[PDB]
Amino acid sequence: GITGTWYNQLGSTFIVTAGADGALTGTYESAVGNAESRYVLTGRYDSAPATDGSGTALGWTVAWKNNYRNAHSATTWSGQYVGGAEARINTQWLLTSGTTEANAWKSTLVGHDTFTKVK
Amino acid sequence: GITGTWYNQLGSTFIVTAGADGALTGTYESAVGNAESRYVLTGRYDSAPATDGSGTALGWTVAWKNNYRNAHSATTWSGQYVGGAEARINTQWLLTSGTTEANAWKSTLVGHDTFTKVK
Amino acid sequence: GITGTWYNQLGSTFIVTAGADGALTGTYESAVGNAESRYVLTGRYDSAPATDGSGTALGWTVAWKNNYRNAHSATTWSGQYVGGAEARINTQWLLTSGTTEANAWKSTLVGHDTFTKVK
Amino acid sequence: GITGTWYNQLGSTFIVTAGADGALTGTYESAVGNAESRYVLTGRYDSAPATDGSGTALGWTVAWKNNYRNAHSATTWSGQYVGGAEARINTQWLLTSGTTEANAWKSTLVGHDTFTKVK
Image (spheres, rainbow over the protein chains, first blue to last red):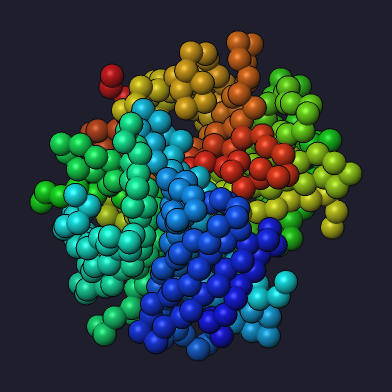
């Protein structure tokens, strides 16, 4: 059940809606980008995973811009949905900011975020 | 001019179509995922960047699945479009495969890809 | 107290010995490199951190080679020692394997490891 | 010939001295850490690589602290020495700064650096 509202341990609220073809839409809120606004994501996942155990490998992208606030950056998560009694999404991510050619070494960040359904 | 057909130094062909709202669609071909097939991406970029020099921070996601071949993985690029006379997209990326809980340490890869318009 | 024996949640045993100049020596065991052998690390940390809260930013490197087994790879952790009543080391890492020029896209891995003193 | 003075395309000067056991010492200068000072590295590489083509997988660590200036950070490169007529070191890296628990999401950076012998 990849469709639903996912949370974090930090406090981020991740509302997603999967697709039959393999698309992935929803909204996103609640910092690393910027705390109090509602941002839009899009992404993809494979529709036919393995059945002798695997994770449904997915990923999405949030460009930090809406009608409230612009942060001139973009964040892309890349993880998998681990299936079980306890639903779990384990992701790496990358935050890329808009810099000049001189400051191009400090543009991209990295990290890890772990998602769950209950909060 | 972010809309168009982008290439690599490896040989990957990246056909993209931007949006006025901030969406990003197109196709993708030509390995790291798997060499000879045509894969679908989606992603986002900010619609209002800075004018006293910056890069348009973007990112997209390819789930390696189509009618020809499945690789059970997903790749997310996260970079910026550097504007000038010579158009340039400089990206980091992450390849996340579908593994079990035991092999969860070797699921995610990392790298860097540099894109251009001429080939 | 950065000097001592650190553990993981996976099961890796990390015995380290700090230095007054800023060096960092010890041993390492217990997979991602290869499970049952004893590998050698070296690394550095800054000797004068901040006192109005910070983490002692450190990092080290293990080349997976000893008298028992060779894996033709190297792993570099890069994190910080968060000070408190509960000692904590939070790290990113990179596993770089020895590949040819053709397979140079899949050489480097990435992940995250969280270290503690009690097991 | 891994022992010697390596350069970059940015301008960083990397003087290294290898070891027979597998150690790796030298100095480092010339930004991402901080521009005009001389920093100390340490690292490791495997002493017995493959002969049917491979890269000598290495890695090292610089803690940005000396008698001139402190930056409260650490950088770890993780790459391979590609052998040939044109010597080449291709690395990923991670810059980890000293942050509090609140700003722990923006501590680690990421990038890529490509090293050569001629400048």
